[PDB]
Image (cartoon, rainbow over all chains, first blue to last red; front, top):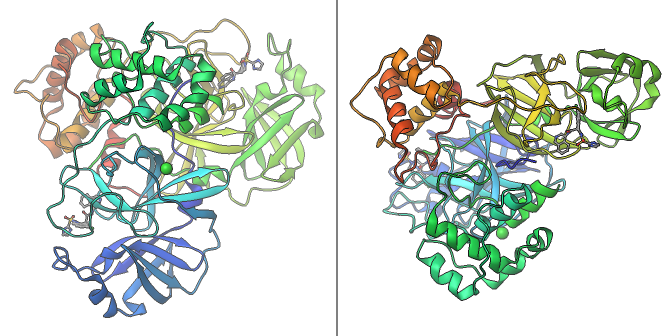
Length: 302
Length: 305
Ligand SMILES: O=C(Nc1cncc2ccccc12)[C@@H]1CN(S(=O)(=O)c2ncc[nH]2)Cc2ccc(Cl)cc21
Ligand SMILES: O=C(Nc1cncc2ccccc12)[C@@H]1CN(S(=O)(=O)c2ncc[nH]2)Cc2ccc(Cl)cc21
Ligand SMILES: [Cl-]
């Protein structure tokens, strides 16, 4: 019993964190085999922030301009290349602590763990979700750039995010490990704003199924809804549309608890109308949307 | 910016997790140097768990009855002893991944990270607080026994908790690494219930300071209060009494934000009597009490390990 926001054990990722210095800028890098991955904005001089020409700034660099530090050991850079918004620094030592890994690009609503780092040193681990507006509500300070997001299903680490910047509203933007940004963002200090954020409907439903599995049934009702009627109500509360894929995904949880997806949808419609009336669901007074259907099956059933 | 429930990096602890099997029971052990620590209830059976004489049960067991598995390697047990509610299994191999460590006993209100394991394999890390009633609101299933709680200070791991059981309300009970239970609990199948819980006042105040640091100021007011008047209000809402030590501890946060501790207490008093009125603080509609004043400073400064 119990339901906590849980992060993956960070050990396999801690053994990959290094410090990357170029000029006056110091940020984090991810050392896998003989390559160190880091945000390409490590080559920028702040005056190269409104309109940097990264190809022009990178052509002027040599291998010895990048100082890479793994613990108390300096790594020698023997090559460098840019792939989208990530800089790939070839080094002369393969990381002996390199775990089994993959680079995965995630979709909004997906969750992952973040190992927040400063000067190549891990300071904390927390659970996150990719918001529908492609931002992440993280906990980051200056020097956290290059900190990574990951999932560890089995013994394989799937790297899905690399932190690049903070938006004016306090939310964070970044890329996958191939350098492609999530959302309409660019690694430039230009006027950029996160789009209006919405609640991840499929995740709230999964969390209501976790509450039922843990014995909380107070919010259930005798009603059902059509998918169309639910979406017309949901849109008015800034909830993401629920698709037939989401309904299919919730199938195992519906079978385990005996509550049809569209019946659980009718309970959510009512919770949005009534509020909680001083009550809580799984220790929360708000509807939680950072647990996916997969997270619920993993944490509630092993 | 941002304020998340954050746990310590778990790597130094992952390298210590092993599986311990005795008879039909499998749970987790902590391998430090040449000793494996685990709950003593790993030696219990069906009727033994009802009313157990653990010295009588341990005498019947020999070293080869304890199967210890570190990854895909079996460790050989060369001795065994009991210290309070923890079993200490002497092994032939010293853990080469043993970090710098200490065994510390924590006080209610203090927080720690828990590395939840099943069959000696870590599956998750989460942050939590020792409740004033000595329970933890954790997330555990069968096989999680022996999972540990810890804090990291520079490069030293302070082990403070070992999971032993789940109470009927879904909350958890365990011991420090010396086998002493937190709370009035015993390690056996019997009628046990967690006492009435209270809110950790110093932690709520620290979390209100974190909200101010992150730009949330709506709850602030022009008023201040006395420590006595605040505690008379706090006792009414099942909040732990706030001591002069708590006030002293919140000092750095008071200086950084310009909000005196009794000035923030007046904000907390108004919040308890009037509610949030549809508003949230750091994305929460409830008053959060699982961040200590040190957690707030550490997260709002970027301390690394
Ligand atoms: O924002 C960034 N990184 C951070 C990362 N995470 C959380 C932060 C919290 C607080 C401060 C920074 C944070 C960096 C640096 N900043 S900055 O601080 O405004 C700055 N301007 C001049 C020197 N430093 C501009 C910027 C612009 C574009 C890009 Cl791609 C990265 C970045
Ligand atoms: O509760 C305990 N551990 C657990 C640990 N964490 C979360 C659990 C969730 C769900 C089930 C157990 C959980 C154990 C197990 N049992 S039990 O459920 O009745 C049981 N009987 C046979 C197998 N399992 C009571 C018990 C009594 C005394 C002691 Cl010290 C430990 C314990
Ligand atoms: Cl995905």
